[PDB]
Length: 35
Image (cartoon, rainbow, N blue to C red; front, side):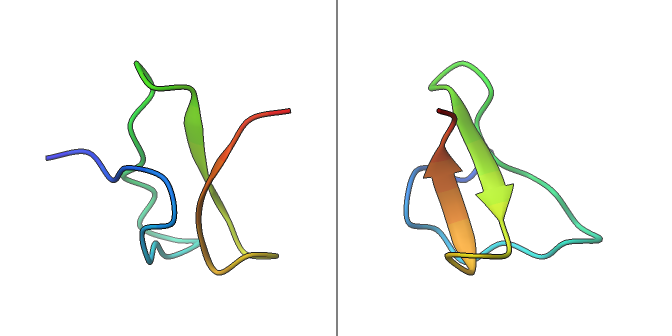
């Protein structure tokens, strides 16, 4: 399952939802919308 926004994600294990324009960001420590 993909990770929605504000979801704890790892820099080595990226599993964010691409259909919802979300990407794992180490700055926020979780999935963040792509600017």
